[PDB]
């Protein structure tokens, strides 16, 4: 429906970056530019140095001429790795020729879109990520949508959510360029406090001002909503090490005491690399392509010392509560896993994160018996003898969990150990 207004569609087809809108913009790729052979078929650039990648798109002057001066929208998927809060300034997508046009850059925790009328004046709008919720850096895939009405407002959306909006000021003289250059270029004197990478996927430009509904329909249509994602937004996969974390306790890592899995406070936030890792193993599912999907039935393995355990329910020293059963690490055969450690996964994405919900499976079928949550309980594990101790543990609420169905305490994330 809105495709009728699409004037640029930068995509990777047949291992070749090209415009598929129909207006045949010219695409030139120079330097260190890597193309992903599998979905999402993104192209990767780096702040590298010598031959840092560079993608140049030159469109039709007339097409630009009869669109950019009224209403237009820019949309694309992007990922920046190690987008730390004190990152210096970088221009990443530039369309400024003679000190006029538009540009997209980053500085600190900000992503900013600039309308540049001349070397002396400009107007910009921005998105600043929540530092407290992204201590290890905002290194996840996110969907950008910038809408501009030269006689109205300039608005920026992130993952379909309106972030900022401002009335476009008088910018007479602004001359839009028909060239767009994708390249990570450092901006001098922007607080150089150190090499970063950037991934771009499906860069589109529409000759209209996309509204909220349009934006979100676009957002969703570019995703395979039943494929669960890891913390950075990549497809979640079986047979791969991940750090399993609960959205409510990002500063906790997985440890073990006796039969129980317990969560400890991590040392710092420069990484998520602390504690034991889990490996997801498939039991049941429609497609069988290594990717973890919605209604799949699966289980979790983990290597502690030089032995491997599977996550499974166990009997605590004392009852923890009505309909509550702790989840631990057990060296058990498959028949036991099917009864006490099999889960049905469901993707659960929000503006803030890519996550999932895990439901206890009934004998490895798609029939649900409970939901996986987390909480602190006082009991005894391992060598505990004289007293009970509070342990933050993964716990399953059996039959009655309607209220938990909406709790973020049931949202689990997976950070690739890589």
Image (tube, rainbow, N blue to C red):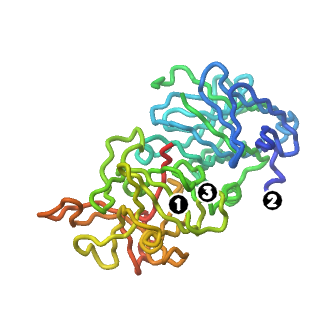
Q: Nearer the viewer, residue 398 or 405?
A: 398
Say left or right for 177 vs 374. right
Q: Regarding mark 3 in the picture, which secondary structure is present there?
A: loop
- Is the N terminus in the top left, top right, bottom left or bottom right quadrant? bottom right
Name which of mark 3 and mark 1 comes first in the sequence.
Answer: 1
Residue 372 coordinates in the image, percent (x, y): 42, 68
For residue 281, which numbered disc appears in the image? 1
Q: Regarding mark 1 in the picture, which secondary structure is present there?
A: strand
Can residue 232 be spotted in the picture? yes
Report the Cα–Cα distance between label 1 and label 2. Answer: 41 Å
Report the Cα–Cα distance between label 2 and label 3. Answer: 31 Å
Say left or right for 180 vs 145. right
At 48% across and 23% down in the image, what residue appears?
192
Residue matched to label 3: 291
Q: Nearer the viewer, mark 3 or mark 1?
A: 1
Residue matched to label 2: 1
Name which of mark 1 and mark 2 comes first in the sequence.
Answer: 2
């Amino acid at each position: 429906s809105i495709n009728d207004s699409k004037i640029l569609s930068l995509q990777n087809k047949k291992n070749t970056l090209m415009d598929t809108s129909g207006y045949n913009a010219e695409v030139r790729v120079e330097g260190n530019v890597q193309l992903n052979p599998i979905f999402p078929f993104d192209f990767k650039l780096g702040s590298s140095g010598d031959d840092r990648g560079k993608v140049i798109v030159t469109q039709n002057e007339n097409i630009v001429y009869n669109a950019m001066y009224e209403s237009f929208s820019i949309s694309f998927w992007i990922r920046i790795n190690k987008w730390v809060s004190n990152l210096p300034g970088y221009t990443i997508i530039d369309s400024v020729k003679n000190n006029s046009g538009w540009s997209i850059g980053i500085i600190s925790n900000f992503l900013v879109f600039t309308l540049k009328q001349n070397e002396n004046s400009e107007q910009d709008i921005n998105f600043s990520y929540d530092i407290s919720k992204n201590a290890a850096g905002y290194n996840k895939w996110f969907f950008v949508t910038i809408t501009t009405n030269m006689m109205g407002n300039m608005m920026i959306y992130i993952n379909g959510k309106l972030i900022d909006t401002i009335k476009v000021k008088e910018l007479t003289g602004i001359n839009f360029s028909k060239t767009i250059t994708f390249q990570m270029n450092k901006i001098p004197n922007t607080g150089l406090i150190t090499n970063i990478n950037m991934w771009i996927r499906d860069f589109y430009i529409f000759a209209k001002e996309l509204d909220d509904k349009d934006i979100n329909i676009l957002f969703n249509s570019l995703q395979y909503t039943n494929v669960v994602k890891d913390y950075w937004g990549n497809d979640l996969r079986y047979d791969k090490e991940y750090y399993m974390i609960n959205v409510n306790y990002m500063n906790r890592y997985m440890s073990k005491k006796g039969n129980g899995i317990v969560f400890n406070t991590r040392k710092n936030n420069n990484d998520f690399n602390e504690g034991y890792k889990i490996i997801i193993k498939r039991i049941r599912g429609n497609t069988n392509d290594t990717r973890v999907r919605g209604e799949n039935v699966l289980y979790f393995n983990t290597t502690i010392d030089n032995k491997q355990y599977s996550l499974g329910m166990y009997k605590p020293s004392r009852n923890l509560g009505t309909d509550l059963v702790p989840l631990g690490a057990l060296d058990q055969p498959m028949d036991e896993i099917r009864k006490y450690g099999s889960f049905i996964i469901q993707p659960c994405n929000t503006f803030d994160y890519y996550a999932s919900q895990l439901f206890l499976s009934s004998n490895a079928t798609t029939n649900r018996l409970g939901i996986l949550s987390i909480g602190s309980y006082s009991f005894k594990l391992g060598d505990d003898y004289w007293f009970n101790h509070e342990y933050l543990i993964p716990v399953i609420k059996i039959e009655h969990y309607a209220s938990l169905l909406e709790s973020t305490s049931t949202h689990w994330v997976f950070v690739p150990a890589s």
